Each structure stands twice: as C-alpha cells, then as structure tokens.
Amino acid sequence: HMVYVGTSGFSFEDWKGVVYPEHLKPSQFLKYYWAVLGFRIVELNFTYYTQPSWRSFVQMLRKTPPDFYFTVKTPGSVTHVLWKEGKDPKEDMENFTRQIEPLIEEQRLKMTLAQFPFSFKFSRKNVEYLEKLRESYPYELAVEFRHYSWDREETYEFLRNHGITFVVVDEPKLPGLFPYRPITTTDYAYFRFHGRNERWFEAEGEERYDYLYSEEELKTLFEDVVELSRRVKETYVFFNNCYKGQAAINALQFKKMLEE
C-alpha cells in the first residue's frame, strides 16, 4: 500500500534559495530532488517550452537510481483540443505511446495523466470522447476534471467500467470548479493539490498557483490519503502549487507526515 509523494516538475529557478541551495546548478536539480529532498516520484509534462526536454530527461535517467519513478501528462491535443473538434485521439496517443514506450518497459512510468480544462464539460459526446481515449491507450491511465458538471454518479461508474484511475483534486473553493472527492475507481489512487488561491480565475500564469497549504489543511488531506491508500496497490500524491517552491515545502511537510 505504498504512498509516493512528489511535486509537479522539479526544474524551477524559483526554488533556488527556497528548497534548492542558492548556487545549485540546474543540471543537478533532479539529483538534488531525489537524493537530498528524498522524493521518489515526480509528475512531468514534456513540451517545447518546459524543462527538462524529453531527450535531456532520458539521458539523465541513465544516471538515476532504479527506485525513482514518474507520471506523465498526455499531449495537450488529447486533453485540450481534439474533443472540441470531434477528433479521435488514436493517432496522437499511439505516437505518444512510442515516445514513452522505453520507460514503461524499464518500469519507470507508473501512470499517465489526462487533465482536462474548465471548458471540458459533462456531456454525452465528451464521455464518448473519454471512451475513444481509453481504447487509444492500453496502459495505466488517470483522469482529472476541472468543471463542476462532472461530479455525478455516472462519471464514476464510467471510470470504473473502463479502469480509469480517478484524480482526487484539491483546488480553489470557487464557483464552477471540481470539488474534492476522495474516491477510488481502480486499484490506484492519484491526488493532485493545486492550492486554493481565490484569485485563480484572474491570475497570470503560475501566480494562479501562489498558495501555501497550512499544516491544519495538510493534516486533513493526509488522513484521507492514508485512508484511501489502504484500499489500493499504490497512491500517487503530487503538489502543484509550485510558485516560489511552495509545492516543495508542502510536499516535504506531507512526506514527513507519511514517515510516521
């Protein structure tokens, strides 16, 4: 019933003079992340504007110990585009599978994440789209919704019928957003904590994720994580409030709680 806590990404300059030493080189960020901060997992989103690149990650992986794992976001087309256009994610996900085929075979990849935007709403066509995604990708899959319309029984029945792991989310407590539902649809749990910034809908970029969970709220989240973890093979917990290392601070606080 292992629980793996980490953060969304590791490659931030914001973190220098917070959780990374002032004078740490960016090429030693990943080593510092797993060797010193002690995180055994990280959630990644490879783009052409994010660090690390896919190439630089796969080379740097050869210098990473066997017991370091990760989860990965699906391409942006699959979660933010094709469903708006009535298109099948088959070609995009098969292409994507090839990219990450290496690391599944090397047992480094624990889960693939499909996180959908606010504009993705509960409808018959969008559920149909989720069925197209499921059949395009035969490996461990997890789904997160942003829109409130999705928090209904039919959604959990669908996930359960198709073996999709439900992403338990903590987000701002604001109109329209998906609530915190500590529920399992599979034999894995997946938690994502974005913080609770009340300015979520106005904020520029990762100023949206400017939030630092209190010890009181971490404790309430923690008791749910341990309660669920007993019902599943493994649980993956990621902190996404990465603005100025807040995610790392909270993830380290949370990791400490797990240690007793």
Image: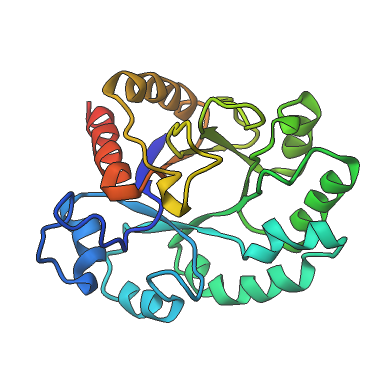
Task: Identify the coloring.
Answer: rainbow
Q: Residue at x 45, y 22 (%)?
A: 224
How far across and down, in percent of the image, does residue 167 sit?
A: 57, 39
The answer to whether residue 92 is above or below residue 147 is below
Q: Residue at x 47, y 54 (%)?
A: 205
The answer to whether residue 103 is above or below residue 253 is below
Residue 144, image quadrant = top right
Left or right: 81, with 139 as reference point? right
Total marks placed: 0
Q: Residue at x 49, y 68 (%)?
A: 46
- Identify which residue, 107 or 131, lies in the foreground: 131
Residue 1, image quadrant = top left
Left or right: 133, with 123 as reference point? left
- Identify which residue, 142 or 219, lies in the foreground: 219
Q: Quadrant of the C terminus?
A: top left
Left or right: 208, with 181 as reference point? left
Q: Residue at x 33, y 30 (%)?
A: 213
How far across and down, in percent of the image, does residue 87 sit?
A: 85, 65
Left or right: 114, with 89 as reference point? left
- Identify which residue, 56 or 161, lies in the foreground: 56
Residue at the outermost front position: 202
How far across and down, in percent of the image, does residue 127 sit?
A: 83, 44
Residue 54, image quadrant = bottom left
The answer to whether residue 217 is above or below residue 54 is above
How far across and down, in percent of the image, does residue 240 sit?
A: 42, 45
The answer to whether residue 143 is above or below residue 72 is above
